[PDB]
Amino acid sequence: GALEERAIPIWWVLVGVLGGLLLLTILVLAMWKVGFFKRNRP
């Protein structure tokens, strides 16, 4: 009810967000490196 450890792991939430952000950033930067966000298609 309160004592219980929902843990409302604000930290894990913060971690998840930061992590999701890092993953998005890396995928984004990587995709940018490989040119995927890029077109220059024929």
Image: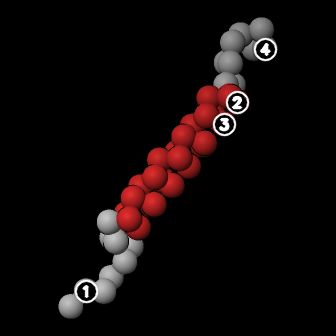
Mark 4 sits on what residue? 2
Which residue is at 60% across, 43% downward? 17
Q: What amino acid type should be assigned to the residue bearing mark 1?
A: Arg
Left or right: 23, with 11 as reference point: left
Mark 2 sits on what residue? 10
Q: Residue 23 appears at what percent x and percent y?
A: 47, 47
Q: Is residue 35 above or below residue 16?
A: below
Which residue is at 39% across, 73% downward? 37
Residues 2 and 40: in front is 40
Q: Quadrant of the C terminus?
A: bottom left
* Gap in angstroms between the C-alphas marked 1 and 2: 44 Å
Res. 13 image quadrant: top right
Left or right: 42, with 38 as reference point: left
* Gap in angstroms between the C-alphas marked 4 and 1: 57 Å
* Gap in angstroms between the C-alphas marked 4 and 2: 15 Å
Q: Residue 34 appears at what percent x and percent y?
A: 32, 66
Mark 1 sits on what residue? 41
| Circle 2 crowding by C-alpha within 10 Å: few under 14, some 14–19, many from 20 | few
Q: What amino acid type should be assigned to the residue bearing mark 3?
A: Leu
